[PDB]
Length: 207
DNA sequence: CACTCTACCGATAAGCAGACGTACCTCTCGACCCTGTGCT
Image 1 (cartoon, rainbow, N blue to C red):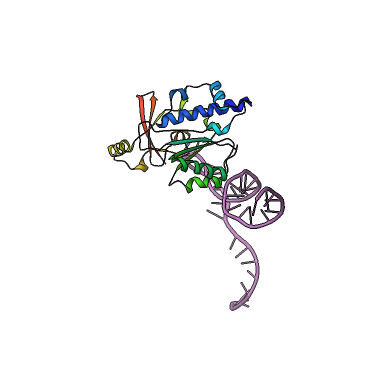
Image 2: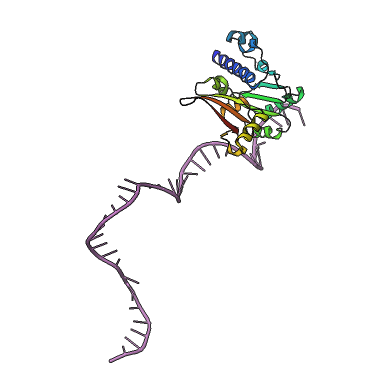
């Protein structure tokens, strides 16, 4: 019982960090909470976690072009087509451009088909709770990934006289690509340490 | 308009087979059968 509560708290804080990293607005109070505060703000009198209140949303911080982002934790342990349609409806109602759905156990394939069905209208990204318990970008092995704006990508390609296919590649299913919400064609500048040069800048296109 | 019996395309793995293997060099030694048919 308590284990599920602490797991959902960890996933929820990780989702808040994920939102803040992508460039959306998350108040420092939200980032710097504690387990007890989460219990107070999301658990009932009987301490039973209330999955209705696990959803939140955020606004872009420095790029007003981006739409609002909406994050919801699946009420049912396994997401189905019914809940996928419900989530798409919720996204449409409030005009949320981006939507992240976090489920616990599994998600059906025909439910996944809905993501491609509405890709032209909304961008929907799915996470498993276990994929957000620990923030991977805080790992020592993970170097600093930074999304490049289209102007900076164009600058890089023109400087190296490159084609997008000639850059190193990063998979869309890459954990850090999913953490950063990378779409196909977007380039990430990765800053790394180096035994030889001290610091190194690699560039990977999402593909 | 609550149900529970079959249609579905899905995914699941399942057992399947098929596919691969250091470098360069020196030398020796062994290599079809079976039966028609003209010849004498």
